[PDB]
Image (cartoon, rainbow, N blue to C red):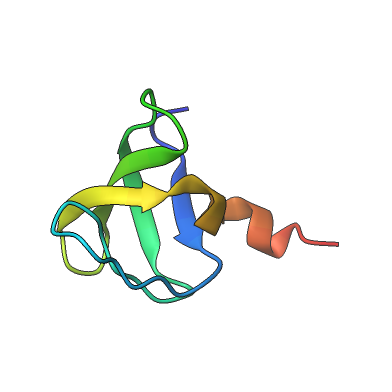
Length: 67
């Protein structure tokens, strides 16, 4: 479960240093998902770490499997 990579479905502009800003289509490694609707993630584009809203991302593999 930990090695599952995720992809942003929507753009997001963070308003605090602790959160990541990202574009739709950018991919993430999830560092911690045990504190609620906000996951600690690493951006696979910049390498920055921060919290992301989990409802903005989906498993990368689920894109090709979309109906």
